[PDB]
Image: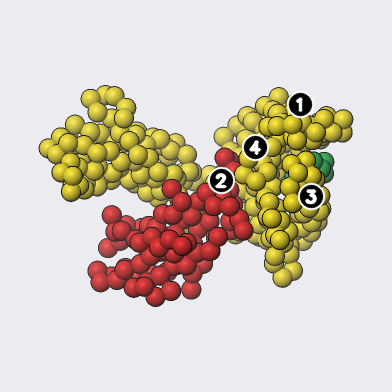
Chain colours: A yellow, B green, C red
Amino acid sequence: SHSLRYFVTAVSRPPRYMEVGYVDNTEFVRFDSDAENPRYEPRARWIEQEGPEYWERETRRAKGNEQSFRVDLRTALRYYNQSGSHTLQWMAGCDVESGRLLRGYWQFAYDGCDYIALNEDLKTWTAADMAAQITRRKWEQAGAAERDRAYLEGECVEWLRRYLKNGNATLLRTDPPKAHVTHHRRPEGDVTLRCWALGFYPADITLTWQLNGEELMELVETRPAGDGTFQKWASVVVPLGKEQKYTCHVEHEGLPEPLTLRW
Amino acid sequence: IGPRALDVL
Amino acid sequence: PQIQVYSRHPPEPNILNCYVTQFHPPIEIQMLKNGKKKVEMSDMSFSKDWSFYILAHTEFTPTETDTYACRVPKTVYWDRD
Ligand code: NA
């Protein structure tokens, strides 16, 4: 399946406003209030084809969003009895199989913490606390969920489909992980094995160590390589002389066959 | 095109 | 883990990355070579769990001699491992 997602942040400062858009794990647009002439801008080649009307509609939506988020920030201050800087984050996204909407998201956090989220039914809200219950009641009364659903099932699906056509050359690729194991004897006398997956796209991957058929492990987060691809590693500490009993297993949509690696 | 957060907190 | 430093390709013409996560905007990031401060920054964003991230990156030819790091105050060194 594929997703189209917007990640939005507003930050009060003793207010900066940013939007980023992604298809799957590729950023394709960005808006930043602190720019000299703030406007929506391309971050992938394939979106530059779009006409002037695309950019101006997007810029104007961003600017309206900015104003809504300034009110949001101010209101949240009141609900929580605060005086400092504060962040409101929003994510809105559709996940589509090949036209059916697998899953829709429309959710917010305040100061890094869950605030409110549209449920999987795309009809009801989950509020994190009694402040967020005030929003949930107002949004119930305004029919917010119906309009948010119509975006997620309508415009979001139709635009993802156009992006996937526009950027087909880059968006439909699957870059397999190139994997290897490194070995490091520790001054404590035992051995660190680390299983690396490099150069893969998309970001989703499974990386695990096994011993004698049983899953085991420090595992890092998928980190960007900077060129559109991802990296990940997983580590185990193993007794000296026992390295060969350990196998690293990697699965990723881009692979003819799951990888099994050993030192 | 993209999403509008019309409804305020 | 809030700071990771690593190369785009295994080193043997490459890019060094400094990847910073779990911070609370509004963070400062400096890359260093042999202790001495053209660094491109990604757009800040956040993960589905609301955790923020940013990538600072720089062009470099790795040498057996040279040390690199990223200062965020914490200096974190590039281990070629
Ligand atoms: Na993609």
Q: CA distance from mark 1 to mark 4?
A: 18 Å
Measuring from the top left, give residue C74's x and y in whole percent.
Answer: 43, 61
Look at the image and tell me in which quarter the N terminus of chain A lies: top right
User: Does the beta carbon at disc 3 come under 8 Å from ligand 1?
Assistant: no
User: Do discs 4 and 2 share a chain?
Assistant: no
Question: Mark 4 and mark 1 in contact (Cβ < 8 Å)?
Answer: no
Does residue C22 lie above or below A15 as drawn?
above
How many numbered marks appear? 4
Q: Identify the residue position indicated by label 2 in the image.
A: C51
Q: Identify the residue position indicated by label 1 in the image.
A: A123
Tell me the kind of residue under disc 2.
Answer: Ser
Q: Identify the residue position indicated by label 4 in the image.
A: A114
User: Do discs 2 and 1 share a chain?
Assistant: no
Specify few, some or many for label 4: CA neighbours under 10 Å numbering under 14, 14-19, or 20 or more. some
Q: CA distance from mark 4 to mark 3?
A: 17 Å
Q: Nearer the viewer, mark 4 or mark 3?
A: 3
Q: Quadrant of residue A211?
A: top left
User: Do discs 3 and 1 share a chain?
Assistant: yes
User: Do discs 2 and 3 share a chain?
Assistant: no
Q: Identify the residue position indicated by label 3 in the image.
A: A74
Query: From this viewpoint, is residue A26 visible?
Result: no
Q: CA distance from mark 2 to mark 1?
A: 26 Å
Q: Quadrant of residue A107?
A: top right
Tell me the kind of residue under disc 1.
Answer: Lys
Does residue A211 lie above or below A172 as drawn?
above
Measuring from the top left, give residue C69's x and y in whole percent.
Answer: 38, 65
